[PDB]
Image: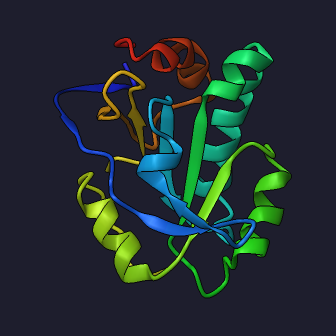
Amino acid sequence: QAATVLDKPFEKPDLVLTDTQGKKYDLREQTAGKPTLIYFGYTHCPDVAPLTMNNIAVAKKQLSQAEQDKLRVVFVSTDPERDTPAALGKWLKGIDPQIVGLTGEFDTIQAGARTLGISIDPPGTQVVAFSPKSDAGYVLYGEDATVDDYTKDLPKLIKGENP
């Protein structure tokens, strides 16, 4: 299976970053009680960033618009010097306009990623799913995950069930 299900789920990082509208976005508050998928990467990546987002987006498109509206797919930029709020927003809008894009100080972002076992250097686990039941990071996906894996697993992730 692509999914690694954690017996000891991670805390959602306490990130307060800038969203694509230039507004302060408290990750924990904004996504509280919502199935949330987080990815750290950068919009100038021609491979992993756009493929991961597109895999999730295509999977998400299978769901009813009501279930889609429950999900929070969060892209946290690792390259804030290019991924300004509005630049990040433009790039995401061409994949799915519901994806939340967060940008801010690299040190803050790197530290937040570390609390999920994810190592980011300036330009392993790729995506962490957070359960709506606990807000804890209970499933990890790596680069090997395909559109088919996310398609199969998203309805379970939405409910906080094991995939």
Numbered disc total: 0
x and y percent of residue 56 in the render? 63, 34
Residue 19 is drawn in which quadrant?
Answer: bottom right
Residue 62: x percent and y percent? 75, 16
Spot the residue most to the left.
8
Q: Is residue 34 left or right of residue 133?
A: right
Vertical arrangement, residue 9 with respect to residue 149, above or below = below
What's the image's color scheme?
Answer: rainbow
Q: Quadrant of the N terminus?
A: top left
Image location (x, y in percent) of residue 159: 47, 13
Q: Is residue 25 above or below residue 143?
A: below
Q: Quadrant of the C terminus?
A: top left
Q: Nearer the viewer, residue 124 or 82?
A: 82
Q: Outermost residue toward the bottom?
A: 81
Regarding residue 162, the answer to whether it shows in the image is yes
- Residue 151 picture location, percent across and down: 61, 18
Judge whether residue 59 can be spotted in this image. no
Give the camera-side residue of 79 and 48. Answer: 79
Q: Is residue 112 left or right of residue 54?
A: left
Residue at 34% in and 72% down: 110
Q: Residue at x 61, y 56 (%)?
A: 49
User: Which residue is located at x 27 percent, y 51 percent?
Assistant: 116
Question: Which residue is more in the foreground, 116 or 141?
Answer: 116
Name the image quarter holding residue 4: top left
